[PDB]
Length: 523
Ligand SMILES: [Cl-]
Image 1 (cartoon, rainbow, N blue to C red):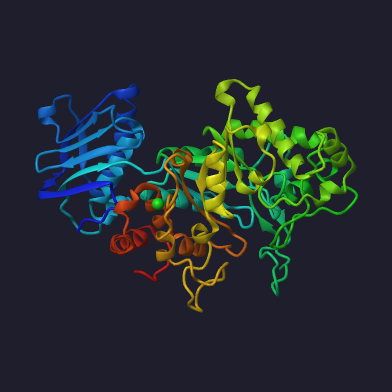
Image 2 (cartoon, helix red, strand yellow):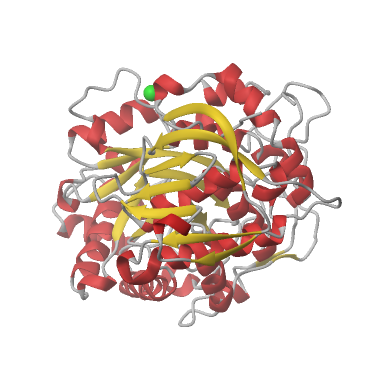
């Protein structure tokens, strides 16, 4: 009957049910300039769409069948939800807490409510009596989509946001730039999208698959970006842009080779292959430095969240070793290790950001390869996204006083096959990254108590070398996304895969109402 995902920290089931009727009154705290009333108004619209129930306002506790009260002692995303025959009572300290209480309230109702779809026939509406106290284990509960390899577009990304929101995920990491495409309009550099957002193959070549000649691509205008940011904010999802530099930058190099290429006399094209490119940005070129500053400036206007991801994964130094500007810069920073140029490039950008007014400053996230360099100049107010040797990298980050986010390739890359069946779509892996394998990863296993404060959370990543169509994206995303969401939210002691399996089965109905694809193996 009751199926909540993520499982709350504390749930007690009580006798009886709360019945709505067609109309009822709510009393809602005015905290923070009526912000909670605004959250509640959004909820009311959803509820009416799905059920026909109308909620009006009251100031009188005695008339309130739903009450949202401020409890400042609760954590920033925590809530209490008490459902009795007489009243629904919610307590929280911050808008996100109240929003999550209402997510859990929706999830206690038939699945059409969470889906935001009315039922064909006439229905009766109620809640089970419960006492819930809930709070997320981790503050960062993320999903990353690669749109550089294949582009999905606004409608599909809204569906991604919708999926994340079901499971209380709060961080969308937008991997917008790659060797094979650049997907975000930058006004000062129009060729990033004019050249970089189109290429002459849909498939990315690998093994026996060759380029297919199709004029393929797409990008987001700044208007598009602002729309998606606003859409996600309504669901308490913040967006982190990733401009992956100076590696994974062949599309940018193809757009502006005259100053971004290490070897501008050679040819530079958007890459049609899968793999790791050596065609990295010439970090020693002054126009490359200005380019990066100017891109960051435009990101700052589009993305209000306080973090930017600069990537830094899989960045070969060989083209720097062969470039005169780079050799000279390395000599001038007193080094014989070309990796240091990557760190210096970042230091310039970090310094630049520090010159800006406080509200324009951003904190930086990097893939963990950056930690292999001498990062001392960057200080410890950077964040390491741990993916390769993740457990060890996160521990090293924490030991250096850096925040860390866990996105281990195994098992949190949910583009990978989720079954060994021969009928699975083509993607990376053998089929070992089953729902169970995802759920069973324990992020803080054997992590010393003193390091744990630096572990900000977890993220599932979705790489799109092989994935070109929304149906396949969704098939691979779901239901593994929910396992990572639960890992991010639910206390480890309350996590149980067989229990999760029973609960997630109830969401097939939700997925079907929304027309989402999903793997059916555990269903
Ligand atoms: Cl754990």
